[PDB]
Image (cartoon, rainbow, N blue to C red; front, side, top):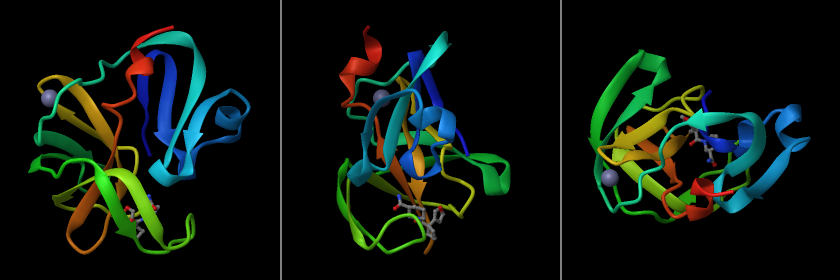
Length: 140
Ligand SMILES: NC(=O)[C@H]1CCCN(C(=O)C2(c3ccoc3)CCC2)C1
Ligand SMILES: [Zn+2]
């Protein structure tokens, strides 16, 4: 579980979005596993605007933050799960690390701010849904 809180926006994994999120929808993309809903109160997360490939992510299944090197956002095959059929997920970055069901929503951060959130796992890899291209998160 986990979310990003920036301005009047809440960014969560689309597959974990609640009834309150769909009832206050701003934007969603199934191919990216992202959903953004509106909030009443202003958030304090800063979204990174950079091309960093090293950062630190939170792993809830270990109660630990791990420093990782991660790949550039790309179209990557993700196996079928209870949430999506087998498909290419876009804007996804991989790192070598631990990610289990329950870890989605953990933040990945670099020196510039929030880079993305955990979206995939297994086989000793962790995948993060990038949010650095969503420039509109910083305005209105
Ligand atoms: N974005 C997606 O399509 C993911 C939806 C949730 C399940 N996905 C995973 O990668 C798995 C996982 C392991 C750790 O966290 C998640 C489930 C076993 C691997 C795929
Ligand atoms: Zn950065």
